[PDB]
Length: 92
Image 1 (cartoon, rainbow, N blue to C red):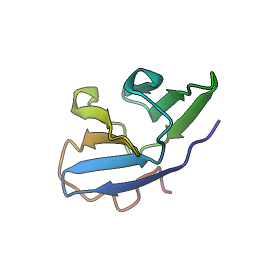
Image 2: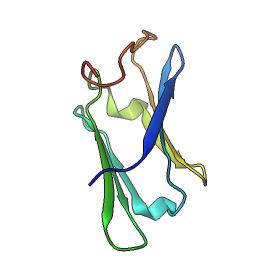
Image 3: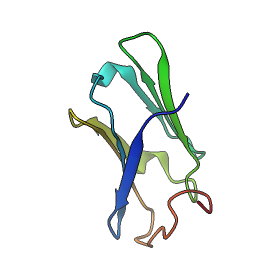
């Protein structure tokens, strides 16, 4: 599948906003395991709305978190070093 999303980053944190409201925490299966950022939103409506974000570089899983804001889902991953990921995705 695909989902509507946008992103931002500090000189420290990479922050991905999945632009989804029809959701609750339990729906949002985010996995980080030194690969891509796979965010599988199991919709109320049964189906999975999934983002597979091919990160510029894999990161230490422990640096990774997420919260359902309400109107969006904010996934955050703290960059191991505070370098600007000029391009979020693998040469996006």
